[PDB]
Image (tube, rainbow over all chains, first blue to last red; front, side, top):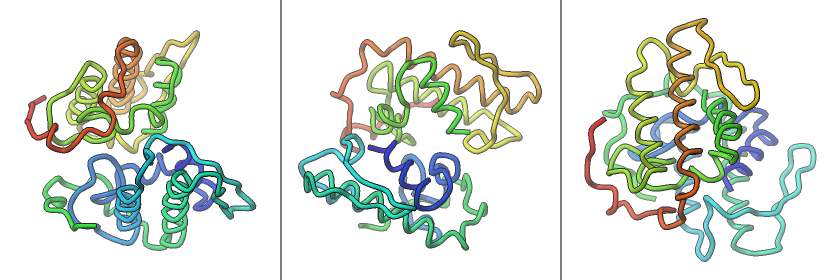
Length: 121
Length: 121
């Protein structure tokens, strides 16, 4: 569930997803569409796509089980569907962390005109 | 800031915004198109519109000052722009609270085809 995603972002990237990644580019935030603007934005695009590939459970709603060790997330294999959700969230959190050097407020609150026809997954 | 919106929702409505309102109707965790599907969805629509009227500060990002006693939210008059953000978030949290009894999973994950109509603010 997206609260768990927030927690993983905090554990892995050392910053809040809701604070910093909720209005970024074309995909980090609600109503994502268009083309990813930078690496951080692509992290969100990939996350959306990852969620779209999860079948048999609800990736935006269902809770998953995981452990965290000093910023290292282990998605538990108690249920392959919810593990898939967890792996989506873990991957996105890692992607935000790995691209922290190009995070840029240039991409905050960008005009509607910047996000039009969507890159397909 | 959206983290503060979460705090207001949690206190006022008694449940998490990120958990329960990230994929509801055409506007809760989505937006940009459609007509509100029920009263909860309309809360989100109105919140989007409210944010749309904010001039001079960034409603998704900027932090506001508020106090809370016995579950009330008093948006501080230290800055009219951030107070306006606060009031938007407060109104939405109240709206979620007031409509919690009709909150229904009927409106989870609705197809894009259900959100093609356009309703102005």
